[PDB]
């Protein structure tokens, strides 16, 4: 049996840690819901 | 049990201790999470039970107690916030500019942030606080890093 526990509110927070790049990737989604890179 | 709107941890006791297997959003009495988190199994919320209502393996999404309620979309230009709820760690908002998963059926937003697999289902937000999708289904790029799609469902 799985159970849920509250972790917080859903709000936009100003001055949050800004990180991560923005790559453009050629992908494919299969019938099992798994993404793969197309090359 | 607790049906207050917000972000929640999805825990399991089947394994050692209490392990976090994913995250979800409670909105308008509906719990929204990734399919690979629960496999469509029932959830507990204190003494109350939550039953699956809609689910799809290909989309990798599942809703409990009602139909999928989240319908905000990424505008394709602005930065977003991943409200990452990692196992054993406090919820933190990480601001990022998404990339693009180019597919044969159209382009989809993508957040290039690495978090443990149990962070799956954490919401991605717009500047208005609206849930534009869930984090946890994507690809592993050349250096072992994870790039997740911005996964959103359809509001019927
Ligand atoms: C690469 C690794 C560190 C990592 N894996 C992940 C995953 C992950 O493996 N998700 C997953 C698993 C099973 C099935 C599906 C749906 N087809 C998605 C989710 C979030 C962050 C991650 N970081």
Image (cartoon, helix red, strand yellow):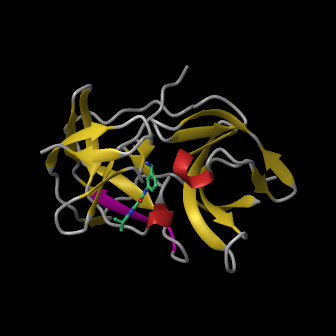
Task: Give the residue at x 57% y 51%.
Answer: B24
Residue B85 visible in this rendered orientation of the protein? no
Residue B147 visible in this rendered orientation of the protein? yes
Q: Principal SS element in the magenta part?
A: strand
Task: Give the residue at x 63% y 28%.
Answer: B67
In this view of the protein, which residue sits in the foreground, A14 or B81?
B81
Q: Quadrant of residue B9?
A: bottom right
Image vertical order of residue B85 relative to residue B109, above or below: below
Seen in the image, is B119 located left or right of residue A16? right
Image vertical order of residue B76 relative to residue B40, above or below: above
Q: Position of residue B47 (x, y in %)?
A: 87, 56
Which image quadrant shows ligand 1?
A: bottom left
Q: Position of residue B59 (x, y in %)?
A: 45, 36
Q: Quadrant of residue B116?
A: bottom left
Seen in the image, is B13 located left or right of residue B56? right
Image vertical order of residue B130 relative to residue B113, above or below: above
Q: Position of residue B152 (x, y in %)?
A: 43, 36
Q: In which quadrant will I find the C terminus of chain B?
A: top right
- From which residue to which does the magenta span run? B90-95
């Amino acid at each position: 049996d799985m159970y849920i526990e509250r972790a917080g509110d859903i709000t936009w927070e100003k001055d949050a840690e800004v990180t991560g790049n923005s790559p453009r990737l050629d992908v494919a989604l299969d019938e099992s819901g798994d993404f793969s890179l197309v090359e | 049990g607790e049906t207050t709107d917000g972000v929640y941890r999805v825990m399991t006791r089947r394994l050692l201790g209490s392990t976090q297997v994913g995250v979800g959003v409670m909105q308008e009495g509906v719990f929204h999470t990734m399919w690979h988190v629960t496999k469509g199994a029932a959830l507990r919320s204190g003494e109350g039970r939550l039953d699956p209502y809609w689910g799809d393996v290909k989309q990798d999404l599942v809703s409990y107690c009602g139909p999928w309620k989240l319908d905000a979309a990424w505008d394709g230009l602005s930065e977003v916030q991943l409200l990452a709820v990692p196992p054993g760690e406090r919820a933190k908002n990480i601001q990022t500019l998404p990339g693009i998963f180019k597919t044969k059926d159209g382009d989809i937003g993508a957040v290039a942030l690495d978090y443990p697999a149990g962070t799956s289902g954490s919401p991605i937000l717009d500047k208005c606080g609206r849930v534009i999708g869930l984090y946890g289904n994507g690809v592993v790029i050349k250096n072992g890093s994870y790039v997740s799609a911005i996964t959103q469902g359809k509001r019927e």
